[PDB]
Amino acid sequence: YEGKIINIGGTIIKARLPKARIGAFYKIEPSQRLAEVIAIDEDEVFLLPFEHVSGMYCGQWLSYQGDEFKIRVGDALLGRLIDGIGRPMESNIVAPYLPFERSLYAEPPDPLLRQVIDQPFILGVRAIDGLLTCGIGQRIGIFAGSGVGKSTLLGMICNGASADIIVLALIGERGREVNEFLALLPQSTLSKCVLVVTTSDRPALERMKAAFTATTIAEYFRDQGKNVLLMMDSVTRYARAARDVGLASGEPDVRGGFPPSVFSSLPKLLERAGPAPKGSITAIYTVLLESDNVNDPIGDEVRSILDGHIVLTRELAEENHFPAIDIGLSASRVMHNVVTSEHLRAAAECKKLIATYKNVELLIRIGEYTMGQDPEADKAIKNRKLIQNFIQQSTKDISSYEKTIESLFKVVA
Amino acid sequence: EGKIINIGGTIIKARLPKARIGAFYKIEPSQRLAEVIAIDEDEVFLLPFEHVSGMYCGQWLSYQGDEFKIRVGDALLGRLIDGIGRPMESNIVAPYLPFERSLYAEPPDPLLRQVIDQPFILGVRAIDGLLTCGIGQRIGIFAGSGVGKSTLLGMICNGASADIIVLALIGERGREVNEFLALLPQSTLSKCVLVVTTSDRPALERMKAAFTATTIAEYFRDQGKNVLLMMDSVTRYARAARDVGLASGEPDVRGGFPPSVFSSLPKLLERAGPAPKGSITAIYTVLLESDNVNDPIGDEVRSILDGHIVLTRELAEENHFPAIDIGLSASRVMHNVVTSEHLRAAAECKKLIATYKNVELLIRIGEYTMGQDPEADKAIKNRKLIQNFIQQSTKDISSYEKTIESLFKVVA
Amino acid sequence: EGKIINIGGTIIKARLPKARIGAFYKIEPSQRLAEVIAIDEDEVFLLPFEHVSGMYCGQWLSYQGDEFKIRVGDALLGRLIDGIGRPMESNIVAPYLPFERSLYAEPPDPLLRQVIDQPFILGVRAIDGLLTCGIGQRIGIFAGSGVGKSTLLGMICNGASADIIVLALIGERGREVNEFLALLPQSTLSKCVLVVTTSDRPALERMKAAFTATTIAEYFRDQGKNVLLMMDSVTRYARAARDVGLASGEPDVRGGFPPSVFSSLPKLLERAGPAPKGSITAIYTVLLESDNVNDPIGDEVRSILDGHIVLTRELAEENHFPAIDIGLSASRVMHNVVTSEHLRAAAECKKLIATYKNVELLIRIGEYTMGQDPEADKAIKNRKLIQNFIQQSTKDISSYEKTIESLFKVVA
Amino acid sequence: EGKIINIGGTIIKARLPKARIGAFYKIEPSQRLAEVIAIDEDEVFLLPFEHVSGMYCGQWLSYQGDEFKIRVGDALLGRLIDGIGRPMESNIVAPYLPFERSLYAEPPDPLLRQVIDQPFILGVRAIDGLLTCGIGQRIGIFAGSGVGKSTLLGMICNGASADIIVLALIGERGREVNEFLALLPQSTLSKCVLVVTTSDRPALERMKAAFTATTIAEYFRDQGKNVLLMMDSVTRYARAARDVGLASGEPDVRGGFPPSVFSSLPKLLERAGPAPKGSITAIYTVLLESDNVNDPIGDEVRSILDGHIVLTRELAEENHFPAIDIGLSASRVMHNVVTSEHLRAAAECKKLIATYKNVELLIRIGEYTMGQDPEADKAIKNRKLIQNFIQQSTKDISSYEKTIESLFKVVA
Ligand SMILES: Nc1ncnc2c1ncn2[C@@H]1O[C@H](COP(=O)(O)OP(=O)(O)O)[C@@H](O)[C@H]1O
Ligand SMILES: Nc1ncnc2c1ncn2[C@@H]1O[C@H](COP(=O)(O)OP(=O)(O)O)[C@@H](O)[C@H]1O
Ligand SMILES: Nc1ncnc2c1ncn2[C@@H]1O[C@H](COP(=O)(O)OP(=O)(O)O)[C@@H](O)[C@H]1O
Ligand SMILES: [Mg+2]
Ligand SMILES: [Mg+2]
Ligand SMILES: [Mg+2]
């Protein structure tokens, strides 16, 4: 009725329709599909469709629906799967009564009301609780290459950790995995868990807005006053989708691909999940790196945004050192507040023992090390197979927080 | 009805008013085909099905349908298919196929995938004992050029018992069609469809042949069969899509490639997996732009598939065949498939392989004294047993039971 | 017929309507031709055959034929052709060449090719023994500059015994025509066709010489006789196609090269090989842009040809001539054309060379004792035999039987 | 004529209708020529080199010729010529120079350019006895900085056996050219024709100095003499051509260099070889560095020339002048310009050089006893005579029969 699509191809369509707001969405009038206005020029506007672009033609009419895309949240979506758009995935069910219609884009808390985090958030993995340590309210990231340990360690964390609500966002990832995450979490955890699932075949928009859907649901269950655990698998899939949308809309190319929209819109998403006046969100974001280098565009940006980073190395997965986290290269920015002085000092001594062996390792292999002429090299060797049973852990094992402390005190001696 | 206004070398563009995207057209005097890929308000970019030599400005385009659909049916078993669905072998009669299928279908719904828990034996001892294939697992074979990819698919063509074998040979040597017909017996060739487009063929016909292989494998999946799909150098599809996507005016997001080859590789690889009715277990061969595993398409296909088998050139020069690097290889479902003593025997064997590659320069130069480290002596004493368990000739196939009993014997 | 509106150094833009792509035109005040590459509405982008340095704006184009066709006949034997197709011998009267045909031809059908199982005796002893070649395959010589490619083609040209030999010299040192013409006797020159372009010649004639050499070789193939196409530096064709593609407005995708180079190599290299009627055994040399085999164009030619002889500079400096590195090299038909104990002996001789290369540090500074590895003691005992087997001089030639019995002698 | 439309900083545009390409136009306020490089419809591109700042919108041009020409003649001996072709020494008058050559000629017909057969006498005992030059060989000396390039190069100037030497110095400074030409006497400046352009001159004149020296040496070839051309620093020819080609607007293909540099080096240094009348024996210089390792100009120059000399650094940090490392350097045309006994006596000395290198790094750690090998002990007894034969002072010139008999008394 209003405008006409004049340009079809790639990821974005372009239509002639005047007096368009930005962000408002539009039904393709003979086709039931609908599209969001992402960028406006004088009379031609860039739209981004929700579905496939095939089948369209020039002059196809474009009706009007709403001024902002909002999702529909409620208390009645625990234990239930949600799409990236906001719809429920499963069709066996009777549809819920979700009463509260929330906008997708919202504001972080005031920086003066976000209190200092000083309570440890127990995950269950011995390395990431003993050496590094989380806190109720931080947002930690898991940095790895392709197929190293990210989804296996996030499954261990979801198995071991406990929170009032658990929001788990499987964005950009293979469809085989939505049943493995429903398999390894129990019935009591499925009583309090919302999955937000977007497979990698889905369009740019669903794979781009599923992260904002999961963050909005976590903010809703925060505002009731509950400690909610957010877990987002491959936030770099959001980054790739924002890349190809922003490049198709005609933007420049800074820091290896990646328009300014990506690096300017990551903190508008990652700053929304932390401590708050009522409740808190403990977010865990996994990051895929374009090589094994940690110094990616997106890897370095997300490392400079978050509150702690767990870097997993492929060269430790070649040796079956699982979980493959690299202790010298990873860090946790709040463990000096959330734990006492004995644990922090013992963790410091164990980290320095690991780095000391990593310096001593190569000249043992080619056969030039001499015992006796260095007191702290031998101390890093005499303990080494004792510390590795603390630093590497089976998948079907959870560890208590007091066994972790006593194991670290026995290791560090 | 409209007329061509330029020819660019890869794609053409034309003055078609109000044309559908995806629709294909006949170039009216000379009997060829092209299809719409982009629209600029009256000027459509078209990708021709053939070579572009001979064309001129003002050449008409008659209309033929809204979608290039292939003619599929049950009489494809035992015969060879061109990259866009046509039969190749002119020696025999044209087959009769009843149904039409488009090349672009949706993956099965993620709630209906039913996590894979049954082993798929291959015949290679390294991808039985130390890696293990599930029925529904999609696997990749990552190597450089001439490292052993095709040799290993030839090993696991006559070793894997599946109901329908749909083999795609996109972007490779014309000489090989006969060699992959000289490794398959008639008890295998009677159930094997062999889709093949070679390196000569146009960029559309190497782009749109992996979709033909997946569509045929989905027709044989929906009947209820366990299909074994296997493609040769899916990076030839990736390079054809690079060429067309750069000719159509897209940027260069990573290592040479447009974003549309990164966003259209999952919606080909995600269709081959476990399903409610039937299953497709697929094996994708991936060529790397060097011997680095961190190629862009190598990295993306490693982050899509359910298992990667990395073959290195170093082991090929060492005459260690098949050249599988056990450290860089992984199978994402081995633990859901094998028994637990099998799993810990596999982990101990990979520990022994890594420990020998630690202590090898310590024993060769002469500093390793026999008795210092209580795992390196295990590795040294079991080196040759591990090595003739890992290596295998092309015409030797192993079963599952003999492989795991030799694994238990070698690892302890 | 049309004027010229742009002259750009390589691509000139004529304003002439209804022009067919592939057609060539004359610049009518002169006798120099130009071939159409791309078109627009009424502006065709075309490439001149000679250099561009004498042209002005309004300069007409007479129409010549719609495709560029060389004239081939049976009287090209013993002649000298350039990359356009003209004779170079002014001292000899021009022959009678009744047929004409275009330079762009499809390969044989992939099923009408056959599995090659007959050896091609080169004469070089190392290649014949350890690596070996089949009648109808495409071997490829990879080296640096000045490592010894050309010398090995001269050796392999005196030694081989094909019916017709079509030696192409593309983008090469003009001094060498008489040196490749002096190592041939008259008994081989009477059956050999020689196609010579030079590094001085422009980016079309250096680009079009490979296609005319392969067209002449396909003519003598279609007469039904085993021909031998030897091509000197096919990478000069790759450089010329890079310049033509980048002048025509193509993007870099890998190492400086456009997509059109990587799309135009496989059809050139894939029209040679087996055939229903005859065979065309091809030996291509590839100049790697440094002394490394992971050149973009070196890797893409290795992933097309079936077999590769990788020469190294570290052996050429140490007077290991010819400088074939036996570990880096391969031949994809070795297992198929020769007997089984020959395959076993060659495989463990290659393994013996590799296991000396992983020992010799223990010998140069004294860390090796005799009786702990009997294979290594046998290797150190037999190295003088083997480096009197791998090395041979240029005028040395050995038949196939003496090569096999010397291999059986050299590894016992 | 026409006037300047705009100046885009480096390249300028001017409306000259029906203006050819290659032509040179005269700016009307000053004495500054400029070159057309690309032609549009009625608005040609045009390239200034001297000075850009004092320019208008409306500054005029003036037509001179079809393209640029220089004045060659027999009275060029003992001169200094600019890269334009102007005589640099203004203290004398340019004599009756009657002939009129262009800068761009073709190399001879390769059938007429016949095999090079007789040795070129050079003077330096290393390049004359161990390696050997030829009459028509294009030697390229690879030097560092501080190895003794200019002193050796002056020995080549003075000790040569050629009728005319032609010297070009392409990128150099005034102290550098004066300290070079103050090393060779008036008896050598009688036959020499210096073509000097320095590192303050614009890049067009440094690019044209190579062509100017080549053309005047071809003129001295066509009247039947042995020309000895010496381009100093083709590295800086390549830097000048890179800067011109990038300023014209041309894509980077390899290491910072446009396609025009890589396609302009063969048509430069193929012109300097054997000929049907006379011959020109060329010797180029490339400056290799220690901050690069690839240096694409060094690789391309090594691919186009035939025979190269590597001047290493540590052969100068212990004062071994001339600093030629035999075994790292080689000449191709040696086996047909030397006799057989001189060939076998030359290979023996380089075998002894490599042999004492091996035995010396064996013995200086302490793993050698005197008495192992007679090739080692003959190397021991002949080291002082080898190092006495290779070492040659700045004033010492030897003949060729003395060189052969000194080689025969160093082979013993
Ligand atoms: N802690 C671990 N224990 C056992 N296996 C592991 C562990 N971490 C990684 N792996 C092995 O590595 C493979 C790939 O890990 P995955 O979690 O799928 O990577 P991604 O980070 O890409 O999702 C898994 O199949 C797994 O078997
Ligand atoms: N198991 C094996 N036994 C013997 N040779 C092998 C084996 N695996 C690889 N090769 C060698 O590698 C060659 C080329 O491998 P191929 O599979 O054709 O490479 P690509 O991966 O490029 O298709 C084989 O012809 C053979 O020479
Ligand atoms: N088999 C050999 N025996 C002795 N010398 C050789 C041999 N092969 C090459 N060489 C030396 O190497 C030089 C250059 O080899 P060539 O093949 O011309 O290099 P390119 O590969 O660049 O053409 C030759 O002049 C020759 O002296
Ligand atoms: Mg994952
Ligand atoms: Mg293959
Ligand atoms: Mg050569």
Image (spheres, coloured by chain):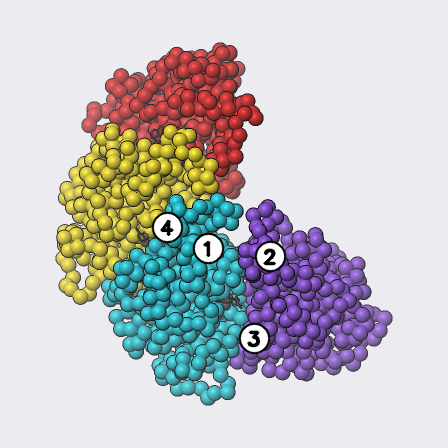
Chain colours: A red, B yellow, C cyan, D purple
Q: Residue furthest bottom?
A: C93
- Badge 2 or badge 3: first in the primary sequence: 3
Q: Are marks 4 and 2 on the same chain?
A: no
Q: Which residue is mark 1?
A: C293
Q: Total label count?
A: 4
Quadrant for ligand 1 reads top left
- Which one is in front, C236 or A371? A371
Mark sitting on residue D356:
2
Residue depth check, mark 2 versus mark 1: number of the one nearer the observer: 2
Q: Residue furthest right?
A: D91
Q: Are marks 1 and 3 on the same chain?
A: no
In the picture, residue D236 is in which quadrant?
bottom right
Give the chain letter at badge 3.
D
* Kind of residue sitting beneath label 1: Val
Task: Reply above or below: D173 against A31.
Answer: below
Give the chain letter at badge 2.
D
Asked whether residue B181 appears in the rendered view, the answer is yes
Q: Which x, y percent locates residue C393?
A: 47, 69
* Kind of residue sitting beneath label 4: Glu
